Length: 99
Length: 99
Ligand SMILES: COc1ccc(S(=O)(=O)N(CC(C)C)C[C@@H](O)[C@H](Cc2ccccc2)NC(=O)c2cccc(C(=O)N3CCC[C@@H]3c3nc(C)cs3)c2)cc1
Ligand SMILES: [Cl-]
Ligand SMILES: [Cl-]
Ligand SMILES: [Cl-]
Ligand code: NA
Image 1 (cartoon, chains in turn orange, purple):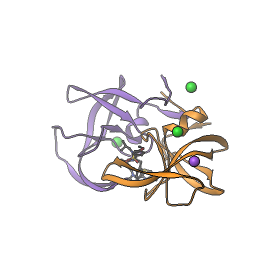
Image 2 (cartoon, chains in turn orange, cyan):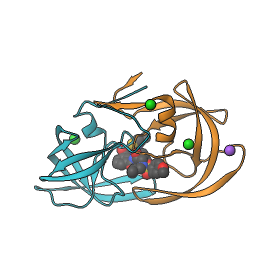
Image 3 (tube, helix red, strand yellow):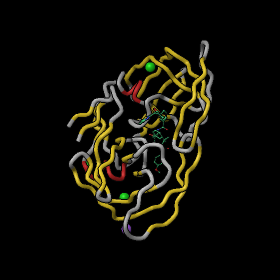
Image 4 (cartoon, chains in turn blue, purple):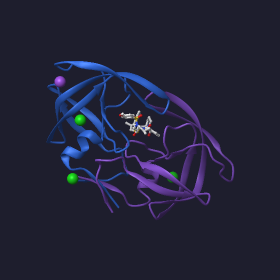
């Protein structure tokens, strides 16, 4: 699809068996989801943005379905105010910015 | 152009006669630039990023070139980890996300 930027680019994702709304975010290196449980191992990480840093859990090899397209990669889980799909998964669904 | 997302989507901007680097950021409603001098009056604004809220200075109707495209609109000045071009100016340069 071609997604307009007149509005926030929100899409439905499926992760861990759960449906969520998430922001397609070209400014995010990594994908960051609000607190939830995910299977398998994880390790702690700090990520920073406006306002400073938060601590997250890094899970590798997690499958997400993003607006109907499956992708696999690392997902960070922690107290983000918004679910963010970052470039590590946008690339896998072939997302580009066009102007 | 068509910009893939394997690398950060960094572009050159020109504001106040100065070239700077900035990140095209579909997850930001607003454009936020590091401390600099801009003309005119400013208004207060709070923005809530991943780590908390910051205060910024809001300047309206500022001339800014983005990747060679002319925009005139609101620029927020404050402590951001990188200069970010948000949707208020991505719409002015005609950007869309596509997959
Ligand atoms: C390493 O992986 C990382 C992943 C994400 C980040 S980040 O979330 O901090 N971020 C990085 C840039 C600052 C370099 C991504 C950026 O797109 C964030 C995404 C983000 C959206 C909403 C809340 C928290 C994070 N936006 C803003 O900072 C930002 C800047 C200026 C204005 C706004 C804005 O429009 N917001 C703030 C709250 C309300 C409104 C929005 N709500 C939503 C739902 C979308 S935008 C966001 C950092 C590291
Ligand atoms: Cl990854
Ligand atoms: Cl590609
Ligand atoms: Cl504007
Ligand atoms: Na894993």
